[PDB]
Image: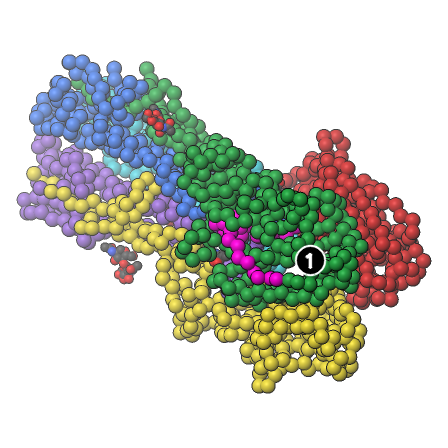
Chain colours: A red, B green, C yellow, D blue, E purple, F cyan
Amino acid sequence: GDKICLGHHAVANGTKVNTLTERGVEVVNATETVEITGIDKVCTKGKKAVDLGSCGILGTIIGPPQCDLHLEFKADLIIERRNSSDICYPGRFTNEEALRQIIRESGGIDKESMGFRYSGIRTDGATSACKRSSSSFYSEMKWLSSSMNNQVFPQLNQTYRNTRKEPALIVWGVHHSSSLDEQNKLYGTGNKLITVGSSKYQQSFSPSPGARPKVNGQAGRIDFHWMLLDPGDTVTFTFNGAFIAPDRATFLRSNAPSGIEYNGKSLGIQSDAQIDESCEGECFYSGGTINSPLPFQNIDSRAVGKCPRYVKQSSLPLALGMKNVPEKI
Amino acid sequence: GDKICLGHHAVANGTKVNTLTERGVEVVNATETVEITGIDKVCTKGKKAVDLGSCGILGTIIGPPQCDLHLEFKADLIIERRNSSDICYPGRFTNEEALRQIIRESGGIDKESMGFRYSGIRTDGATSACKRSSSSFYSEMKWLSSSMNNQVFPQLNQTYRNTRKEPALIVWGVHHSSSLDEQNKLYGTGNKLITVGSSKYQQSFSPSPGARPKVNGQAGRIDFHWMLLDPGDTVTFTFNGAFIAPDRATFLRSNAPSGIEYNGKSLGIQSDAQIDESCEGECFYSGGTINSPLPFQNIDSRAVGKCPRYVKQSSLPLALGMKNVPEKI
Amino acid sequence: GDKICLGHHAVANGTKVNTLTERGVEVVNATETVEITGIDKVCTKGKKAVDLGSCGILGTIIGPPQCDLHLEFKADLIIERRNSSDICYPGRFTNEEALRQIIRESGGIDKESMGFRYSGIRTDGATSACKRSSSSFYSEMKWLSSSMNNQVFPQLNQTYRNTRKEPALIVWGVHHSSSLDEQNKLYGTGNKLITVGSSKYQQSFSPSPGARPKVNGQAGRIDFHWMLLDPGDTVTFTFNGAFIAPDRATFLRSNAPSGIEYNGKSLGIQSDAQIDESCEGECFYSGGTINSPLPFQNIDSRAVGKCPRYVKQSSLPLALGMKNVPEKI
Amino acid sequence: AIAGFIENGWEGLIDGWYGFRHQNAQGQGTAADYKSTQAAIDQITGKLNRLIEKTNKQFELIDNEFTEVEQQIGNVINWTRDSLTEIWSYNAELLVAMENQHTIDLADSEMNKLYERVRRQLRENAEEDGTGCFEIFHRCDDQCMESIRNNTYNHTEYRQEALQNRI
Amino acid sequence: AIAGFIENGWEGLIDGWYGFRHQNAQGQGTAADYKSTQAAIDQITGKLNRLIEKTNKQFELIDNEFTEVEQQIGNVINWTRDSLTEIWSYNAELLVAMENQHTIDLADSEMNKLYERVRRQLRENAEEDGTGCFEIFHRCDDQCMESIRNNTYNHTEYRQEALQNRI
Amino acid sequence: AIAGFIENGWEGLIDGWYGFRHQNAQGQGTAADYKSTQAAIDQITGKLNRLIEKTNKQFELIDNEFTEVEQQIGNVINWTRDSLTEIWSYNAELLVAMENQHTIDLADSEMNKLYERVRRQLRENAEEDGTGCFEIFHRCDDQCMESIRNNTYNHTEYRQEALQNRI
Ligand SMILES: *[C@@H]1O[C@H](CO)[C@@H](O[C@@H]2O[C@H](CO)[C@@H](O)[C@H](O)[C@H]2NC(C)=O)[C@H](O)[C@H]1NC(C)=O
Ligand SMILES: *[C@@H]1O[C@H](CO)[C@@H](O[C@@H]2O[C@H](CO)[C@@H](O)[C@H](O)[C@H]2NC(C)=O)[C@H](O)[C@H]1NC(C)=O
Ligand SMILES: *[C@@H]1O[C@H](CO)[C@@H](O[C@@H]2O[C@H](CO)[C@@H](O)[C@H](O)[C@H]2NC(C)=O)[C@H](O)[C@H]1NC(C)=O
Ligand SMILES: *[C@H]1O[C@H](CO)[C@@H](O)[C@H](O)[C@H]1NC(C)=O
Ligand SMILES: *[C@H]1O[C@H](CO)[C@@H](O)[C@H](O)[C@H]1NC(C)=O
Ligand SMILES: *[C@H]1O[C@H](CO)[C@@H](O)[C@H](O)[C@H]1NC(C)=O
């Protein structure tokens, strides 16, 4: 008797996958869904990248020596490094994380003088902690010291109006000396006060003398404080010592008018890996770059950029063919 | 040959929809799922609404002139406007956002006198920035000035125990004068300190004199500070100048005993649109009201109220009919 | 005629369940998916648990009387109670919640002396608010008072380097006296300042005298302030009065070297229920323990531990059998 | 020449979702089947079932469109929000596509069930043509056709004639 | 008179999910089909598979039921929490409902497969009655019935008698 | 002896997803069916459709791997992130499993449809053997077989021979 049969393929060994009903169902073919391997490079082909090296990203603003080449950077991708420092003379920024976030997306920074001039005082204080040949300071500010040696310190005002149509980033420092001897040696004797006024911002600060553990061989500290000054608005510094003054204001290339020094929002990453101008990626993490066709990744939940979605699972196999049912006898 | 056929409808032209497998499959009928158009009104029919106008919602508490009609409002829906100010004499609240959130849900506010009386001093300081006739002040507080002209200022105490079974909202101000001439002109000469004690709260404050950019022609500022005083608890203000004193405490109608002046939690919104007593809605945004049968919306991810779920997509067509297969020949 | 029929079971009355298409479809059998009942005990079998009783979890650090037995606890599960106090002499921690979180996961705490000795002064201040027999203080600190009665107070330094390879938890207090008479009665007369320096940390503090509502019959307060001092780093206290000094530092058993006093991350819960050594559980809430086979729970969205997922619905019936179709005639 | 659903659909059936088209000596006709039409139409109210997940829950402002919140918490909020948006966008598109598949599949299913039911009424009196029609191997006047449509047809009444014509 | 699954369910089959009911000269009986019952029962372990998503992951307290956290971060937390609750509530209801559809569909599937299998055993010896039974066109005593149930029946053994009785 | 898909799969069919295996006087052959193969293969591009949900949306750092953020907001961030991770992990596993079910089900579906189509071509000329084969009750030479595979076969040309052999 003549006969015709309908049938479908099968293979000796298939791949297990999961369905809704069942687990470990064998199919003719499957493919992985979850990327598990990264590129141990920062893949920078076709973007403008800056490796900030040992320069902490906040350093770009105030300008310790290690940041000299980075005071006006233009970047599509900013690579912070693990060892970085924002400082030379020891100290902290208030709201430090907030600012890091601001710089990371800035697209780079552009500097412009604030036209502060002085006359009564020394405006060139220098430390061994900021070595740039002999001794210098924060490139972008000025350490306002007592003009003689033990001279009480003038009750000075300084004012700067934001000319541009972008926000201006202004930063100033408060000098916490190592001893009350050195404080009134470098400034005046009576209690010292710094008032900083915006339209919006309004708060004040005064100096806490006292010995702290030496950091870069300095017992002193600087509190760094910062504000974004709105277009049109003005800021007034009123101070009688212990004041580290801004010299240049910062602007973010991301808010500039279509012209040179624009960039557009950048992506800040933090990374351990060597740069490679020779590969691409839009997704980064500490170990480097995730460039993958798959839709998920299990490498690093903190990957940043344009990324496969992160999942806790290492493998999620996707069936590319029918249930595998071997040939009977 | 006699014959019977089974068949289903079709139309010449159907709508494309997506399934799981496939994209752009044609069905007899579909309907949209994502609302994309709003009502450009605030739809307030069947609710108690107040348009705070130029009165900032924090103003309701301390009472600058622009807030006169709002010192004891009852509201189901509170409309903040874009231009609003909480102030007349320039300044900020500490923790300003937290408080805005408190008032927004309050259901309105109710005032109660705290019975502070004075005698040594002037308790009627007034400014040109708070014009209500000639010159006045924050309706709900009192500017404690030096009684003569350059008189040092008494070391005063004031105490207020929360009588009610609801929390009381107490707010006080610190006066940062334009110059140290004006400070000790309006108060005493020796350093001035303000200590504010609850059972729970305990912190202090002192005044930072110094010239700031003029705001409403005042170089001065007031730091506004606030506390929620628990039922039973008491609060002590101890101060020697620079003190803007509370006169009435605030209570939230949302915590009142079933009686008049209750309301229940309100919804605070921020909006540009005109009010319309003539339409309803439970979902609001800056452009107005989202009143829609659909389950999703692509209008504004910050819509508040009871809202369609927000989605990035502008259209998600839902099949209301079978797959469309035109008639062959 | 002979006949054979194929058929499936049915029951008189089935259970309604939901599908995708339809609602209230009857199936032969179903089972609940959402746990709605808890165990009204804390189920502590197989773990090391400490019931902190009336001892606030921050008390374990500084050692008010009620916390005597808890100064060096070792715990897998820490039960805060509703009534707890961290204090005897009234006061607050700055950043109090952050620290609570640190202790909760600590696995218990281990103390080690910081080797501060004194000589000029009295270091044995005691209060009636910290009754342990007669009058005492915070077991773990020392109230540095004026040595005589109205003696001005020495300009003292103290330094402590973190020996261990774990972080050290250091806490100190600022004493806000009830009156300026008592302040300069218990200390010196001129303004008093406390400077606290880490490598990282650097800020200062001064005392606000003034009367506050009595708490445990004390108008005074202590601001408690804390730091985590990194391995290798050192901290310097410089102070001239109003200083409540650390005596022992805290370490978290979670960072100790495999040896005794290790534990490993603990789970902190807050609970009303009696302890029961007699039942198990890995999920807790204020009402007790959730120990259940089902995958969801509607009991408490803040349950902590390893927990069914929380859902707003009280029941989600799952079909364990086919659609129910009764027998016709 | 007439054809069933395997071939295609019927632009002329404007009266229902499913229907019968016949041919006999008296001519050619199409009529909607009411019951299966309603059956299909009744499982179509997705819109407020897609909506019945629309919340009991009221949400408030967490940030400020007029006076910007401080940068750090503003970043956390914004991040959280866009995170929830990715998720609801994904949920919405998945729910719609699942509903769309169910609607299409269930339409075929109903058509197939009607077809199977008619085949079983006709027993040995008809053969499937391969296009969704039955060739009926006996005269079936308008009333006989009606009886197939309303599930009244008694195969034994035509069996003998049909068997003869089949063999 | 007996009827199959297309008509309805069998309240009296308490012994299995699926079964055969027969009629012959020796009388009338019902017997569960073990194999297809187990097959169905084996795909029913949803409860701990719905549970196998129950987390490895431990969560800690983020706020405070005893000493309320500061207002702003308390609002962000609360908002985030209610947001995750909307999401899990929606996931839970969707997972259950999908499992429910699968369970119902697959039960029909098994019943239908048993039915198709018997139809194919019987070949030309029997005709579907349209209620889920086969009219058998030859004597089928208890042992012959048994042979249908245990997949032993050899159609060629009765073909000639059955064809005669059909025609 | 040859057997169809109800029994098992064909290890030897390396040319397609589905196919015909025949036996006649001139021997035994297997040929892939191209059309239904492509049909199945065409609904397989899941990888970039699973990927078409891969975001337009760019995310930035919210915390710090080098200089740890303040404890309380770091706890909130961390908690939020792990919460979103639970959710995406759950979505990913559900999406994959649903795609997997659909792929398996739809493969059976296509095989079933090819089979149904052939059954309807053969009309009364063949009987289903119950393994996925048709016993053809007339001589079917290679060219007749080809005509079954390419949907050309004209049943009326063999009906009279086939009916005689069946009865
Ligand atoms: C199973 O599928 C995998 C992956 O989809 C197949 O490997 C691919 O095959 C193409 C066809 O030649 C190759 O060019 C690609 O380079 C492979 N891609 C990947 C990602 O591996 C494999 O061919 C399939 N196996 C069978 C029997 O079909
Ligand atoms: C497709 O269904 C839509 C939407 O449900 C139908 O539009 C409705 O038609 C009724 C009766 O005419 C109106 O009163 C409704 O208000 C309509 N709703 C909307 C949202 O427009 C539409 O007619 C349908 N098309 C077909 C071919 O059935
Ligand atoms: C419906 O299924 C439920 C739940 O699985 C059955 O009840 C369980 O069955 C075992 C078997 O003996 C009992 O010992 C368990 O204690 C039951 N568990 C629960 C959750 O209560 C129930 O018997 C079934 N009913 C029918 C008609 O099948
Ligand atoms: C989030 O905050 C940014 C500034 O960080 C602001 O421009 C924007 O209005 C916010 N985004 C939304 C849609 O809330
Ligand atoms: C959130 O905060 C309120 C007060 O802010 C508190 O009473 C409430 O219990 C919290 N809600 C949840 C769901 O935790
Ligand atoms: C979150 O912060 C902890 C400490 O709070 C830190 O050790 C860890 O790097 C973070 N975890 C993740 C995965 O973000």
Q: Is residue A282 above or below residue B172?
A: above
The residue where tag 1 is placed is: B122
- Looking at numbered disc 1 in the image, what kind of residue is underneath it? Arg
Nearest to the observer: residue B224 or residue D137: B224
Asked whether C246 falls inside the magenta stretch, the response is: no
Q: Residue D165's image quarter?
A: top left
Q: Position of residue D116 (x, y in %)?
A: 22, 31
Drawn side of residue C1 relative to residue A33, left or right? left
Q: Is residue B40 above or below residue D4?
A: below
Q: Position of residue B281 (x, y in %)?
A: 43, 38
Q: Tag 1, which chain?
A: B
Q: Most extreme residue toward the left, as rendered? A: E25
> Which quarter of the rendered image does ligand 4 occupy?
top right
Q: Residue at x 60, y 43 (%)?
A: B66
Q: Most extreme residue toward the bottom, as rendered? A: C134
Nearest to the observer: residue B238 or residue D121: B238
Q: Position of residue C6 (x, y in %)?
A: 18, 43
